[PDB]
Length: 134
Image (cartoon, rainbow, N blue to C red; front, side, top):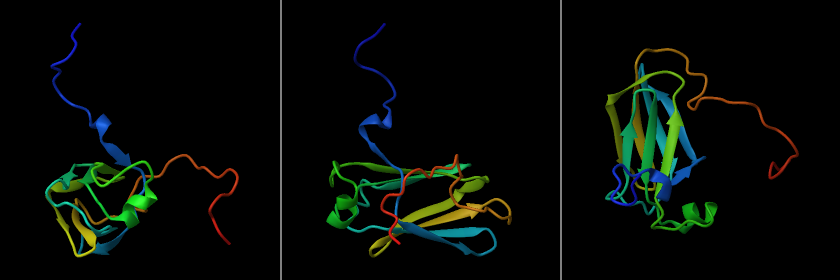
């Protein structure tokens, strides 16, 4: 086949976040603001991809507070946060801008309907308890 000098490059090398401490509130009619808890972020190597039925947030943080949470990684480690929006959206109007110690992402939905959860659900999982402290 072929070895080397490939074309597209998968984010493999990059790390994909599974859970990011943030808070999104229902704004305007179809507006949705998101507040990501993180500091010491690089606005130079940190961007946000607004899809039609999703939205990925790539940013490299160097805050021991945020890093400590994710072991094995570092400040130079790329973090990709992909979210599956149950309902469609308008990325052409979406915007991404970092804040003091948090990130702000304006998500413009299509229509004014109930989302019942920012991120799409999935098979239930309980099993033996863990960190869940009384």
